[PDB]
Amino acid sequence: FNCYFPLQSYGFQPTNGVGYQPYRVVVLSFELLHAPATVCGPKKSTNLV
Amino acid sequence: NIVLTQSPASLAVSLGQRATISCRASESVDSYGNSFLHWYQQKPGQPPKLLIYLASNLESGVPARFSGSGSRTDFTLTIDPVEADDAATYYCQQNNEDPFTFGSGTKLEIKRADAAPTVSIFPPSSEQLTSGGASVVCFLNNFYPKDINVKWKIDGSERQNGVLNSWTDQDSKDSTYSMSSTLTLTKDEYERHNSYTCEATHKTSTSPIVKSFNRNEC
Amino acid sequence: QCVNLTTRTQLPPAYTNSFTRGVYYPDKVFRSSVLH
Amino acid sequence: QVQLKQSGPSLVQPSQSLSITCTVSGFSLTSYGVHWVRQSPGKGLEWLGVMWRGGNTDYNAAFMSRLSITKDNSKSQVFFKMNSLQTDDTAIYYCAKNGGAHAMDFWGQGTSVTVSSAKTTPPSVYPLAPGSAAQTNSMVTLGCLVKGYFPEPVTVTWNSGSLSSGVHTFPAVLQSDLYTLSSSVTVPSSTWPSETVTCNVAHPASSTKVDKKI
Image 1 (cartoon, one colour):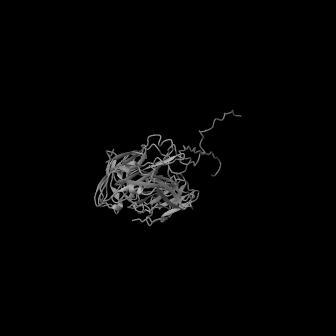
Image 2 (cartoon, rainbow over the protein chains, first blue to last red; image 1 turned 90 degrees about the horizontal axis):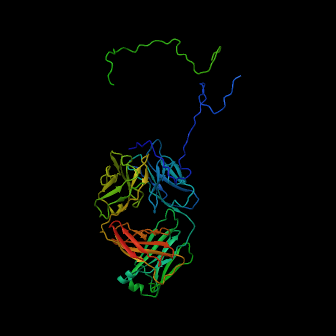
């Protein structure tokens, strides 16, 4: 009586095409706030003058 | 009640072109948050499958060539390009009000190039002749268009009593047609004249399709 | 659990007036001798 | 992985009842509501009903009083009880899995339920064997003439379905309380008359298996 199920399943078969195959996504949400930045890259820390 | 007067009843679209299967509706609004519907496919030589859900989304197992959109009543199913997997009947289904009826059904035909049929005649078996019967079949397969007419002409006089035809629909993959013409008669009719003639007239073959078979073919 | 305090006496919603409270550092930036 | 095929009915007269058994596989009955439809009896595709997940069920406006759904959650099978059927209702009945927006994601093979006052008759198969004078050009066509059966369906295969290159299935010609089914398959000449060839015909309505050597 017109109350659809909000969820729906994906079909990931090995015979799927390039537009249907699964793609594992990892969105690295970077942010630049005024707080001390704890996440950094592997840059060699130098001395201080 | 929703009367999905889907139009047209059939299409003749060649390979690589754009086929348009519209679907007229009357009700209702707010299927989920809009006035969309689902599309389906019923193949003649394969079970049906779901093409498009909510008329805007792709489904796994079928190619992405099926797309479209739709208003409250003016819906559209776009098949662009048309390949050799579309010869089937297409339907549209509303699910926001009981009964969840489907469309009238658009029988899409793949409009390939004209092709002449095959030729094969089968005399009766030993059990048929032993029982007194004699059923000869003149097959004309792998052709386009479906318009084909077989004329069973015995040399004495044309016979049109036990003539039966089996018009097979266009297979989903094989875009050609297939038709079988039978002629069930007695052994006396099969042994009546030395030679016989299976006549037929197809659009592709400008010359009359003629193939003879003799009573001694046993 | 559902054990409600029975010593709670009903009273009306009393209120007062916050004169100049509610100030805080909107960010972790050091500022001095300025009007931000 | 998924199976939603029907079975159980063989032949039914008009204004009578029947019972269908649809075997469900690939998903639990408590997870999706099995739908129920026909296969284009004349006009467009007809919808019959659907049993929701452990609740009530919706039916068609024209089939609510006659047709009913009986869902067995223990055996993983959905049974259907129909009443007061007409000859025009002859079509293949399908079972389908519920989708997100009440869609029919998966579809089964179904069963061709035939409604007709005639009685059941087994097939009198006769093969379409080419004679000794028959010629061949790098290949040979073969078939069988399955005449004198009622009702549909009847599956004709080549050596238990060994061949699949040029197999063509034709529709059944409605005769007087009977049917006539032809077939045509393409096989190279090295298989006939060299190797043993036999027409395999199956009549699921009567569960008859007729073997006739071509």
